[PDB]
Image 1 (cartoon, one colour):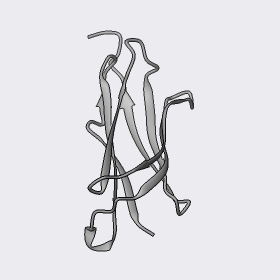
Image 2 (cartoon, helix red, strand yellow):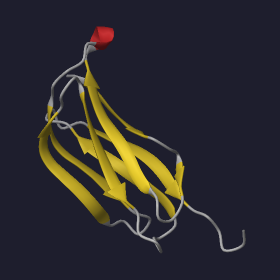
Image 3 (tube, helix red, strand yellow):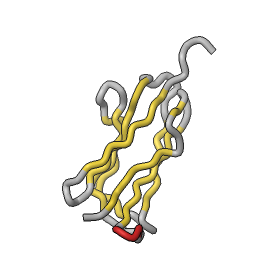
Length: 102
């Protein structure tokens, strides 16, 4: 039983930008944990797993990832999903949008 959570460097990204997120783990008293996470992935508005990293171990209590969005990506709400060994899961949404007219 540890506290894992996800954080993106932004809440809203525009086409062409690289999404950067961090997976963090800690215990009560906020002690950093070098936890081995079984799964973390990004899901787009259509429900696709456009990126996925397996069996990685946190260093210093966290691990950073990045995902370069294409120039014409689906727009709307995405989500980073992390699955911890204990079977617990955590979802962190983020959006990608810009709109046709400036």
